[PDB]
Structures are given as structure tokens and as C-alpha cells.
Amino acid sequence: AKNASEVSELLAKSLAEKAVVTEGGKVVEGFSYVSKAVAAKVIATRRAEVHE
Amino acid sequence: KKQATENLMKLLQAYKDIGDAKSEPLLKNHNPRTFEDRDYPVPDFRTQNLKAGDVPKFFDTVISTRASAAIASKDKFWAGRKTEAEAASAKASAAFPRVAVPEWKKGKTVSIENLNTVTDKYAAALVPKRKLALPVLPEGVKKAVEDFAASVGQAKNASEVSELLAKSLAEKAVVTEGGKVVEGFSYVSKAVAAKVIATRRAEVHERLLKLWAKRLLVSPELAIVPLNEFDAQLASKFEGISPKYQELLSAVAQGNK
Amino acid sequence: LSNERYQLLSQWPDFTTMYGKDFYYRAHPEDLKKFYDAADEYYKLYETVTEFDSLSALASQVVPNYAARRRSTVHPAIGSTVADGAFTNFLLSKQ
Amino acid sequence: KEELKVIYGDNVDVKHFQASPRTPVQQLFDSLKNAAANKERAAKEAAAAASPYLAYAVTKKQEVQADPSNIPFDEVLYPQLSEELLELELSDIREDEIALEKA
């Protein structure tokens, strides 16, 4: 009960991380998206390997 | 026999009391390595006039003398510990609980409501006095998190979303002593302690492999005297060393031509 | 009679409270083997005092010798005190 | 082999568990992956027990034995013993490491 805060958040985040997309309430399946924090990590490593 | 068993149980309480007053380790006095003398004068085989095959039999009786003298020094510890506890066994408490047997009066019968509360006392000592509170996930909360993932539509991977909730409590499972949580109790498990041993075996075995790497880069002819047949060659003088491998080692040392 | 012996196996100290390894390793290795032999002995005594299906064949070792003393040629109920008291009448009368 | 024969079968592969023993979490998840056939074996045995004393005794024993919190962990029970059983093998290795530092 002292660490009862963190034991909930991991259950929240484990569904949040593999959150699926829904189109019209139904799940379109086989939809991979590249996010805006992933795509800004592709840019930041590609900037560092051309700046070096 | 009831008095012999009360004497033995009072003796094993006296052993536990005067070994917890002295705060000694549990395995220390049962380990006969701890009664071994490492500062013994260690007899030199070069002053004992040994012939060729005689040196390993000299090494065995220096070891088995020094091992017998450590076992016989462990026996002298426990024979002196026994009289120390038998003195306190004579001045003891002798308030032990009795064996739970079903209550049977003289002409009466035995109720099953007393045979069962006796069986409850046998299965209440099957629980350990301090245990890990290893949580099973009940179906009352493993379905309340499975369908919450199935309402979002992760019903295909609904198996794995429960197991991580089970394992996250299983991994930081706390210990409980008497139903209450003893707090600040860190334990090192038996899979952690067998990983400390397996890495420590690998970092000493690579020093043995690095030891013999130098000796066979400099002197590669040493690989023709097998390791078990090595001190079967020795003697006390250098001229007494068995010439089984001497002339072969001298010619392998001169190279491949 | 088995109940009077079972009542003194009821008053046997709970040796299983000293089975832990903090009694194993604090104790002399010969006083622990005696303790484990005294616990194996209680199960020998207790498993035979509760063998109550053996009491019905021990009663048949008492019956046939008793029943032959009752097949007396004088009387079934004869004993020494009566047969001595009737020797006093037989001897202390005339011939 | 006998301790793990009741879980992993007869081809238990005792080499894998001698080298790396199972953690207290894997002892838990091997309890729970046979508990449905353990609670049903005890119910089939309590039904065919010879008397209602023995029928309560095979359920009360299974009510304690199927709870994974009742598995006796020697490291939880006796902490000073399992550290000293660790320093029996760490001292056997240390005597082989002093022999190579002298060499």
C-alpha cells in the first residue's frame, strides 16, 4: 500500500504503449504508425551522424 | 522416553541459546575448515628423502594428517560445547507445548470436530514461520483488468496484459513474519546466489586459463607431462626426479627441427 | 488400558517445534541424531497404541486359559477361600 | 530431479536448474500452472477417501500446499544460513584464487 501508486501506473502504461488505433469505433488492424517523437529521434541521430 | 525427549528438547534449546549469546554463525562450527590451522609449519618434501614415486604419497599424508587434526579439533569443540549446554540444560524451563492428539476420554468416543481441529494444528505448522507474500492474482481482479483491455480491444493479447500485473507484484513481493510485514528485510535468493557463484567460478577459471597460457607460450613442452602424472615424477633431490619425461622434455623444448 | 497409555502419549512434548535449521545447526551432531531418533520413536509408540483393531485378538489370548479354569471338576465358582473354609468343616469334624 | 519431476515432466532437464535455479517468481508460476490439476486431484481423492477424517485431511493438506505463499524459502526463513551457504562456495573459489595469485 505504500508503493500502491506505482503498481497502477504500470498497468496504465502497458496498455498505453500498445494502444491500438480505431477508425470508426472498429479497430483497423495492421496499422503501424511512426509517431512524432520517434520521427524526431530519426532526425536527431541523422543530424549527429552528418555533423560528425 | 518422555523425559528423554524433554531432556533432548531442553538440550537443543540450550545449544540454541548459548550459540545465540555468542552470536556465532550457524555453519561455522560444523565446517571443519574453520578448525584447520593454516599457520602450521608445512613439512618440506625436499628434506624427507623421497624417491620418484614417493612424493604424492607424502603429500597425501600431510594433508590427511592436517585434515584429521581439524576434524578432531572440531570434535573437541563440540565435546566442550556439549558440557556447556548440558550444564544449562539442567537449569532450564521445560515449558514445551504438547503434541496435538485427538482428545479421547476413558469410555467415551472421539468426535470428528476434534479430529479435525487436531488436523488443523498439523497443517498450521506446515506454513513457514516467515514467508514470502507471493501474490496470486485472483479472478476477481484478473478479469477486471482483462476486459478493461478487451474494452479497448486488446482481447487477443489479453493473456499477457494480466501476467505483467501478476509479475510486478511477484517481483517486489514482500516477506511477512506472523501475518505482519517485517519491513527492511532484504533476502538474497537462491537464484541470485547461484549467479554470484557462477560468475566467480568463471573469473577464477579464466585465471587458470591465463596462468597456463603464459606457461605454454613460453614453455610449450609442458603439455607433454600430464597434470596427474606430474608430482609422481618428483623427488627430494633434483637428481632423483624420474627420467620418464626428462629426455623427452629436453628435446621437445629444442623446437620442431 | 490402551486409553491409559494413549493419555501419556498425549503429554509428549512437541518435538516438531525444534525441526528448524536454527536448531539443526546450533546443536551437537550426535544430540541431533538422538533428537531425530526420539521423534521417530514417538511415531512408533503412537502408531501402535492406536492400532485398536489388534485389541480384539489380544482378548483371545486371555479367554482360553480363563475358560479352562472355569471348567473345574468341583464347581465353576470355586476358589481357595471357600475350599479352605470347607476344609475347616471337613477336618474339624469327626473323620 | 524429484523436486521438479512433479512440474516439468520426467525429461526435466536437471542441468538447466542445477546451474541456474528458478527464482521465487518462477517457483510461483510453476505452482499456479499446475494448481487447477492439483485442486481437482485433491477433490477426486477426498471423494474416494476411506472416511470423512481422511477426506478433510487431504483437503486441508492441499489447502496449505497449493498456496504459493507457504513454499518454504530457506533464504527468507534463515537469512544468515543462506549467506553462509553462499560463503562455502565463495571460500572454495577464493582458495583457488589465492593459489593462482601465488603462482
Image (cartoon, coloured by chain):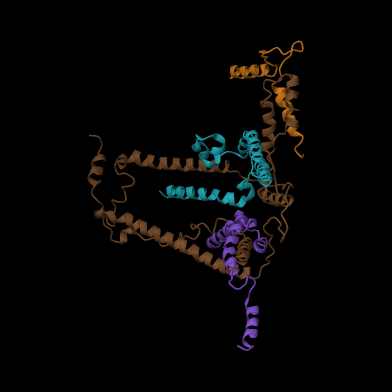
Chain colours: A orange, B brown, C purple, D cyan
Q: Nearer the viewer, residue D25 or B209?
A: D25
What residue sits 63% from the left and 81% below the top? C84
Give the image quarter of residue C15. bottom right
Q: Position of residue B186 (x, y in %)?
A: 66, 46
Q: Is residue B147 above or below residue D101?
A: above
Q: Quadrant of the C terminus of chain B?
A: top left
Q: Residue furthest front?
A: C95
Q: Nearer the viewer, residue B200 or C2?
A: C2
Q: Is residue D75 above or below residue B256?
A: below
Q: Position of residue B247 (x, y in %)?
A: 22, 45
Q: Is residue B112 above or below residue B253?
A: below
Visible in this render: residue B71?
yes
Q: Position of residue D76 (x, y in %)?
A: 64, 47
Q: Nearer the viewer, residue C51 or D88?
A: C51
Q: Nearer the viewer, residue B93 or B207?
A: B93
Q: Position of residue B94 (x, y in %)?
A: 67, 66
Q: Quadrant of the N terminus of chain B?
A: bottom right
Relative to A45, A9 lies left or right: right
Give the image quarter of residue A41. top right
Visible in this render: residue C25?
no
